[PDB]
Amino acid sequence: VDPNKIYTIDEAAHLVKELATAKFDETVEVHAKLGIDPRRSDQNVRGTVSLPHGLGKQVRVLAIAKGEKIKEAEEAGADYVGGEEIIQKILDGWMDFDAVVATPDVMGAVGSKLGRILGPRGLLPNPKAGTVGFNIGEIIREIKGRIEFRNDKTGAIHAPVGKASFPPEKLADNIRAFIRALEAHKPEGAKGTFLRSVYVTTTMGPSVRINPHS
Ligand SMILES: [Cl-]
């Protein structure tokens, strides 16, 4: 619990499981202080990482599909599965999902009816974003691991990387993948130490400082 102690990623992945004391399976997060000034247009860090191990309910997925592809989406573990008939539910205000994926053959209606609704919300299935294809099961599994990140005005950033229930090797894998993605997103122009400090923590537990290069 010593605030000065820097743990390796492997040590942290084992520790966080012992620091998760809530009456529910807590989310594990990585928090970093970045060496950037987010008040500069040329120094924001925003993007996604695809984690090697998907995050279950952390990313609620609606799949819109037809025929055999519906059963494929269900089997892949999409939280909601429907055909074009789900369009009216969304028109009515239903927005309880974190991502939408679809097969090419429903996009006529999805694009025309839900373009102006899901589009601005960054939730419209998009070939360009890898969220429209006939490989709906693969898309679903990938999207369950696709985590968005965005620095706040202080230059701090964070992301969920698992649950306290995860095996430690899976937490470690996801922790490193997230850090690698931050480094991949360093602004060209930022000059000082990029990863100023990095922590692993749970929703309601202590923070454990880590060496992000371990
Ligand atoms: Cl394909």
Image: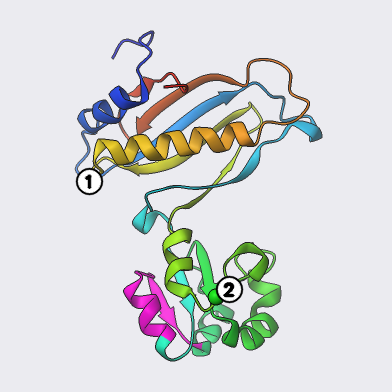
The alpha-carbon separation of the residues under discs 2 and 1 comes to 34 Å
Against 140, residue 169 (above or below) is: above
Residue 93 in sight from this viewpoint = no
Residue 99 image position (x, y, % from top left): 52, 64
Q: Are marks 2 and 1 in contact (CB under 8 Å)?
A: no
Residue displayed at 50% across by 90% down: 85
Q: Considering the numbered disc 2 on the image, is that residue within a helix, a strand or a loop?
A: loop
Against 186, residue 65 (above or below) is: below
Please report the bounds of the magenta region as a residue range: 69-83
Residue displayed at 72% across by 25% down: 37
Q: Going by the image, does 168 lie left or right of 84? A: left
Three-letter residue code for mark 1:
Phe
Label of residue 132 in the image: 2
Residue displayed at 55% across by 86% down: 88
Task: Work out whether residue 214 or residue 91 is closer to the camera in this orientation and state it.
Answer: 214
Residue 194 in magenta?
no
Three-letter residue code for mark 2:
Val
* Front: mark 2 or 1: 2
Q: Going by the image, does 207 lie left or right of 83? A: left
User: Which image quadrant is residue 3 in?
Assistant: top left
Taking the image as four quarters, which one is ligand 1 found in? bottom right
Is the CB atom of the residue marked by disc 2 within 8 angstroms of ligand 1's nearest atom?
Answer: no
Label of residue 110 in the image: none
Which residue is denoted by mark 1 in the rendering? 24
